[PDB]
Amino acid sequence: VYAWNRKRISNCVADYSVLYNSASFSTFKCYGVSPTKLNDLCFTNVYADS
Amino acid sequence: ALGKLQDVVNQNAQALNTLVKQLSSNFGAISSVLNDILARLDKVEAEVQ
Image (cartoon, rainbow over all chains, first blue to last red; front, side):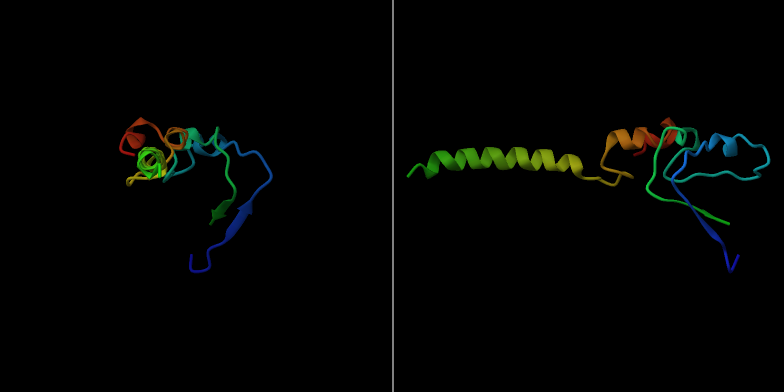
């Protein structure tokens, strides 16, 4: 966590429901957007910090 | 000489330019644009914005 890893995501279609429907995730909280809505949106940049 | 008539046109133009530019102001919401809020949030979160 002191050395946290960022992946850039671009030039693709993102079905976020493949993530937010998975019962594996012990936490899934969103800010400035609702996860229910992500299937219609589009974005300049996407990052995954891990 | 017609400065009296032109002043009335200028004041009415400034009144509408100010009224319309104020649609772009946030007033403390997440965004100035109403369709962006509705395309991003569900009712319980959106109604506060």
